[PDB]
Image (cartoon, rainbow over the protein chains, first blue to last red):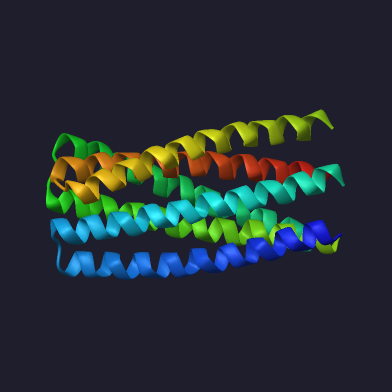
Amino acid sequence: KYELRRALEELEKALRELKKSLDELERSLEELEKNPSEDALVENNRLNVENNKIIVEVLRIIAEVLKINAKS
Amino acid sequence: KYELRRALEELEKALRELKKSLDELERSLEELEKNPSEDALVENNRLNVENNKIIVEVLRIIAEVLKINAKS
Amino acid sequence: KYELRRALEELEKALRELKKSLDELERSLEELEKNPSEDALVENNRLNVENNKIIVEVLRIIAEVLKINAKS
């Protein structure tokens, strides 16, 4: 079952990165609301796109797990 | 199988919240495009971050379901 | 097992759309950082919301797969 175990471990790793990304995104939003500006908006958008990027990777891993389970 | 049932029910609940969040996000975007401004942009970013926040929660639940299925 | 196969095929299709959306989102971000403005920010937000929209659809499909596996 190592194929599945490895996939779930990679999922765990990606979710940890996703959480860190989300934390930074939320911090940026709080600062943006306090002191808004074009620069702060661009910064926040950057971090939002980065969060979406990791979400896409997490979804890829989940799809892989589902395919492993299906051939099983 | 209650562990799995409960997880899938929680998934359903989170997805409903996610849909409401997305609806509000889309409404905000439409208003932003009609009448853009720094304030409207900050508001839209707020709702986008909130949507990402719920997505992360949904992904957590999915990971839990996959772990339940794996020990099964 | 066609129910599951069809769901996984639909998942694959949605993930391909998600990747294209993400690529366009990243391109927009790069241009935004190079030449920022209110218009560019609105454009980037539009593409970010669109990416979230597809993510929600992908999560729906994943939930369906998990429900198929559960009744199985």
